[PDB]
Length: 70
Image (cartoon, rainbow, N blue to C red):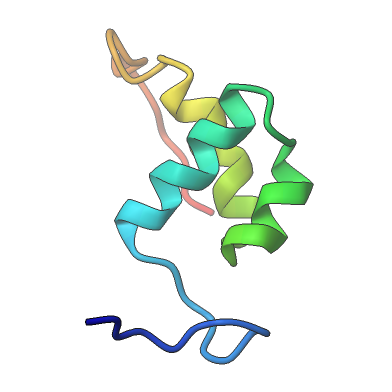
């Protein structure tokens, strides 16, 4: 039985699974980006974008013209 060892930082990365969790809480209004970021261990700049993406821009996305980099 059991297995695991997490808590109080200790390693600093999230699975693509964990990310969906920390989005669903925020979407459902359980918290906001800043709050869940810290709870789930997600970067704010990721979580922010990912909420603002999963909100449903992903269907019929904007791809017609661009010319940029970062």
